Image (tube, rainbow, N blue to C red):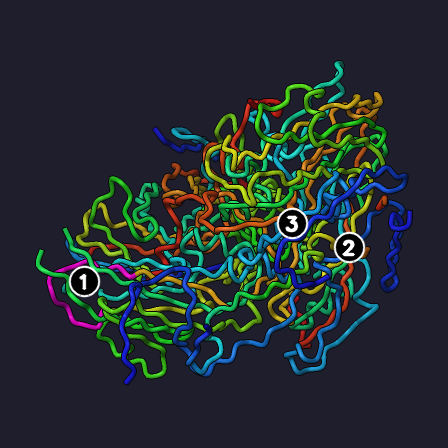
């Protein structure tokens, strides 16, 4: 059908998918550069365009029987990778959107479902203690973390209501990929890249996978492409 | 109704009348009979 | 890493003398603090929990309060067994840090 | 001057009153408004988003297993798969949903509801289901031939992976109440049951146990009235750091 | 009733590995967090890390990343700390304490074990 | 499509429909889009004019009510007759859980202070004069009742009695950003010393309240309750309602009850089986 196939061309990267459903745009918005009337910082921003806008494939994770789910926080996942990660280090501020594409496929004899959701401003909790989560607990870099209790979304909320957020499903019967287009979501027009994370990509297996065919590894691959990147506050790198 | 003798605008009483909705952003957050 | 600065690092007092111990918190840790008493044998015994209250079975010679960012452990009257290394813990946030410690000696 | 006289209700503090009050910061200019995505100007925008029902709630289902319903190949015809109690006020599948959590702040409700079930089984799995809704006034239907008699949809697995069961608005009043009586004529919504229409046929290679995922969302004619405190959140004895804010 | 005792830690050659065993009793083992603290003869305390008993989940101090590995067994009600890259600098007294949200952590403590190396 | 909707939508009658290629009851949830199937296309209906108003579910209506942000009882005797409360909405779970239904909020606070006096465990209930001063972040905090910090030349203060009607002031939206951050993922400081989430530092500052009179008569209990009613509200990005109980006000940490409802493993109370019901 028409919308079952999709191609995504950003920069020197391109992604084709023959099984997909109607790629999602978060809150009916599409990424754009900061307009002049919403600008604050006076220095002329830098716009790498094709340099930093392209798909960066994150390390794939293995989908297994007892998997609880996976999260990647943005930009944090992208801070160490490619020319995007260099502009993050040398510049004090950034504004960009994100295009997230998750690849999970299997044979027509596998059953399973994934909830791929982008949680804006996801503040994580800690189980059975009053101690606030540390820095290394929240910031996993590229590999990302794992849900301890995905039923509560680790923040104490309900996974049942997670559909209020921008989301798509990967149902091993229907489609092998999910695509979400995230605009800039923040209270401030620009933000400090290292400390604050606007979006949290959460892949949760609402329905696990099992089959009576010969078992095989099913990886889950994530490809995240920044869009409409800007940077200010050029200085030396933190490194 | 709506009696404000204060000079500052934020000190006015709350206004309840914004009946605009766009449920289509939450319900149909896509780019676009069988859909597939 | 919120650094707990414990002062003074050492003190000298005689029996029946009121002494105090103050720990500094760079970032505000709220009401979350614990005062730890370690006997010379190596056994640690908690004294004050959440700065507000005392553990059950611990003598009432010990008190605690917060004034600004200062956390004060006040001893009403010293005892022979009360000369040991004291510590202040912060459970407010990870990672948990300990104060430098304070040594108690008898005047001579 | 102007002769006046006080009225009853003078000096009273009413939590819901609407009045203008003296500003504490003269000549203060807030930060200019910036366009931000996802503005909610009415709560009925939220309740129309479908969210997962927990049908499988039991003592043997732990954690996430509670949001899916196991559908296994059955050796007998005309068998009931499961049923959904429709009481939103009571503790049931509809409480933790978006439409449930928001509606519990309101004493009255109106409008149609819709259920959506997604079949997560393997591609080669095929079968027909029937999703029945029985208006109130009687006991839940035990058998399918009794359940057909109400609003139902017969569903066949295929390319489209989901259905929509519309629960129509049927009442003798303009509104219904959340009062604790489950069988009250102003409360009871009716019953929802799911029967095997034919059978679930899966190959020997595919997994035999397949899982539906139930959804529910309010419609465009949905409505709510007479806001109240939500029973969901209860009293909390020990609240950490609350005393720290008082210095 | 409630008690914490960890035996062992006698002599371990450098570069080898050591498995700490701290047993818990007197309460429900999976309802409370487990903490680890080391003390050198220098009398200063450092916080090794904490494992969530509910599952495997662990939180470490940045200095001990990769040096210490925490694991538990829900059956034996014991908590293990795997120390690798053993050096003379790793010789100290190690403690294990309880935790949990209610009534603050570190309500109870262990005896302590002094680790020494033979080179 | 944005539109002005003052009332619920009317229903139109429908007839028997059997047609090939047209399947309104089919949808795809994998697209993440709510089912667009209408009651007219699913079942055979009648024309119904729906006059039910939607005005009461507006966010301006829903979130704007007077709730208790702070309750502080301090004894009045010879001493200490004042308290400094760092302002946050995380204190009481009734208002906290409702404000957390949204990620960002822009609103003006209308603050009300209700004062009551009680007898410690009769002659008369005294009439005391209380001062409530609003100390912004980064200013000097009064350490005493009679201290010089209560002069309050620049600061905003209010004087009110116990007999007079409750004192009420309006607080503008003061955030340095376009809207408040209810949930903040990150750290404020550029070093590791920062705290995860919003900390009682930047936000709204402090509120200092004392009794203006000196110490007289013999001790009574004075409880000060503080109420906040938002106004002019703008809300963005709604969020799942919290289920498990709260633990600390500075973080989202959760535990869960022992048994359902609101248990960690089970939010909804259990039943025998999915087939079980009278």
Alpha carbon distance from label 3 to label 1: 56 Å
Alpha carbon distance from label 2 to label 1: 62 Å
Q: Is residue C40 above or below residue A83?
A: above
- Say whether residue A159 is left or right of residue D162: left
> Where's the C terminus of chain A, which quadrant?
bottom right
Instruction: Name the residue tied to disc 1.
Output: F76
Is there any visible trace of residue A153 in the rendered image? no
- Packing grade of label 2 (10 A; few <14, some 14-19, many >=20) is many
Which residue occupies the foreground of this view, F89 or F278? F278
Q: Which mark is residue D221?
A: 3
**Residue D129 in picture, x, y percent from top left:** 76, 27
**Residue at the outermost left position:** F123
| SS under mark 2 | loop
Question: Residue shown at 22%/67% (left/top)?
Answer: F163
F42 inside magenta stretch: no
Instruction: Name the residue tied to disc 2.
Output: B30
- Residue at mark 3: chain: D
**Residue at the outermost top position:** D76
Alpha carbon distance from label 3 to label 2: 23 Å
- Say whether residue F104 is left or right of residue F211: right
- Say whether residue F60 is left or right of residue A29: left
Q: Which residues are magenta?
A: F211-224
């Amino acid at each position: 059908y028409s919308d079952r196939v999709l191609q995504l061309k950003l920069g020197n990267s391109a992604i084709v998918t023959q099984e997909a459903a109607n790629y999602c745009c978060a809150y009916g918005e599409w990424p754009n550069y900061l307009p002049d009337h919403e600008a604050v910082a006076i220095d002329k921003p830098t716009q790498p365009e094709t340099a930093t806008d392209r798909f960066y494939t994150l390390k794939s994770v293995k989908w297994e029987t007892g998997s609880t789910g996976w999260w990647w926080k943005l930009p944090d996942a992208l801070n160490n990778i490619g020319m995007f990660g260099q502009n993050v280090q040398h510049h004090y501020l950034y504004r960009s959107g994100f295009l997230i594409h998750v690849q999970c496929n299997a044979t027509k004899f596998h059953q399973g479902a994934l909830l791929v959701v982008a949680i804006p401003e996801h503040q994580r909790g800690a189980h059975n203690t009053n101690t606030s989560p540390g820095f290394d607990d929240i910031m996993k870099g590229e590999e990302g973390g794992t849900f301890n209790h995905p039923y509560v979304l680790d923040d104490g909320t309900s996974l049942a209501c997670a559909t209020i957020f921008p989301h798509q499903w990967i149902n091993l019967r229907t489609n092998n990929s999910a695509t979400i287009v995230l605009p800039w979501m923040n209270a401030a027009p620009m933000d400090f890249p290292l400390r604050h994370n606007q979006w949290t990509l959460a892949i949760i297996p609402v329905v696990p996978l099992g089959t009576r065919t010969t078992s095989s590894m099913v990886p889950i691959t994530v490809s995240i492409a920044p869009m409409c990147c800007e940077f200010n506050g050029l200085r030396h790198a933190i490194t | 109704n709506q009696i404000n003798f204060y000079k500052d605008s934020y000190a006015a009483s709350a206004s309840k009348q914004d009946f605009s909705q766009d449920p289509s952003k939450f319900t149909e957050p896509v780019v676009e009979a069988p859909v597939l | 890493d919120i650094q707990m600065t414990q002062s003074p690092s050492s003190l000298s007092a005689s029996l029946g003398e009121r002494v105090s111990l103050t720990c500094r918190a760079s970032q505000d840790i709220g009401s979350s603090l614990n005062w730890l008493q370690q006997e010379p044998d190596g056994t640690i015994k908690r004294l004050i929990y959440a700065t507000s209250s005392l553990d059950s079975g611990v003598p009432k010679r010990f008190s605690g309060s917060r004034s600004g960012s200062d956390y004060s452990l006040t001893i009403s009257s010293l005892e022979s067994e009360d000369f040991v290394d004291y510590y202040c813990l912060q459970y407010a946030s990870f990672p948990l840090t300990f104060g430098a410690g304070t040594k108690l000696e008898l005047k001579r | 001057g102007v002769p006046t006289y006080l009225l009853p209700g003078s000096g009273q503090f009413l939590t819901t009153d609407d009045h203008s009050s003296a500003p504490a910061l003269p000549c203060f200019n807030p930060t200019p408004e910036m366009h931000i995505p996802g503005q909610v100007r009415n709560m009925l925008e939220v309740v129309q988003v479908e969210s997962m029902m927990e049908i499988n709630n039991t003592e043997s289902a732990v954690g996430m297993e509670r949001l899916k319903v196991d559908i296994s190949a059955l050796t007998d015809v005309d068998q009931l798969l499961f049923n959904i109690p429709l009481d939103i006020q009571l503790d049931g599948p509809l409480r933790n949903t978006l439409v449930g959590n928001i509606s519990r702040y309101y004493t009255h409700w109106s409008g149609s509801l819709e259920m959506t079930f997604m079949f997560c089984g393997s591609f080669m799995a095929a079968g027909k289901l029937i999703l029945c809704y029985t208006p109130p006034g009687g006991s839940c239907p035990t058998t399918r031939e009794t359940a057909m008699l109400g609003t139902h949809i017969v569903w066949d697995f295929g390319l489209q992976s989901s259905v929509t069961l519309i629960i129509p608005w049927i009442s003798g009043s303009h509104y219904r109440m959340f009062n604790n009586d489950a069988k009250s004529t102003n409360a009871n919504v009716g019953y929802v049951t799911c029967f095997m229409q034919t059978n679930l046929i899966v190959p020997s290679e595919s997994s035999d146990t397949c899982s539906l995922i139930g959804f529910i969302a309010a419609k465009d004619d949905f409505s709510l009235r007479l806001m109240r405190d939500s029973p969901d959140i209860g009293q909390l004895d020990h609240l950490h750091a609350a005393e720290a804010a008082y210095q | 009733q409630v008690q914490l005792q960890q035996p062992g830690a006698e002599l371990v050659m450098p570069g080898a590995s050591v498995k700490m065993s701290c047993k818990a009793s007197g309460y429900t083992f999976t309802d409370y967090w487990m903490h680890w603290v080391k003390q050198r003869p220098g009398q200063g305390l450092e916080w090794i890390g904490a494992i969530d008993t509910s599952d495997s989940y662990t939180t470490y101090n940045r200095k001990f990343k990769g040096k210490a590995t925490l694991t538990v067994d829900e059956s034996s009600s014991t908590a293990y700390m795997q120390l690798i890259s053993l050096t003379s600098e790793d010789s100290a007294v190690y403690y294990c304490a309880r935790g949990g949200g209610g009534n603050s952590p570190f309500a109870y403590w262990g005896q302590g074990t002094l680790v020494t190396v033979s080179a | 499509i944005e539109s002005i909707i003052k009332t619920a939508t009317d229903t139109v009658k429908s007839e028997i429909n059997a047609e090939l290629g047209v399947v309104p009851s089919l949808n795809a949830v994998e697209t993440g889009a709510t089912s667009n199937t209408e009651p007219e296309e699913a079942i055979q209906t009648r024309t119904v004019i729906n006059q039910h108003g939607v005005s009461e579910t507006l966010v301006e209506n829903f979130l704007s009510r007077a709730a208790l942000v702070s309750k502080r009882s301090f004894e009045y005797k010879d001493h200490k007759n004042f308290f400094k409360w760092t302002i946050n909405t995380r204190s009481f779970v009734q208002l906290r859980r409702k404000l957390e239904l949204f990620t960002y909020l822009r609103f003006d606070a209308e603050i009300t202070i209700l004062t009551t006096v009680a007898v410690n465990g009769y002659v008369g209930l005294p009439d005391l004069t209380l001062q409530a001063m609003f100390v912004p972040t980064g200013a000097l905090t009064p350490e005493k009742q009679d201290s010089f910090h209560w002069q309050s030349g620049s600061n905003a203060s209010v004087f009110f009695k116990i007999s007079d009607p409750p004192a009420r002031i309006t607080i503008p939206f003061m955030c340095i950003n376009s809207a408040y951050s209810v949930f903040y993922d990150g750290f404020a400081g550029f070093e590791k010393n920062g705290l995860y989430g919003i900390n009682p530092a930047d936000t709204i500052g402090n509120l200092c309240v004392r009794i203006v009179n000196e110490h007289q008569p013999v001790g009574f209990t004075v409880t000060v309750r503080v109420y906040m009613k938002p106004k002019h509200i703008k809300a963005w990005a709604p969020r799942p309602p919290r289920t498990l109980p709260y633990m600390s006000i500075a973080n989202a940490n959760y535990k869960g009850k022992e048994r359902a409802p609101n248990a960690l493993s089970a939010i909804i109370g259990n039943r025998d089986s999915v087939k079980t019901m009278p």
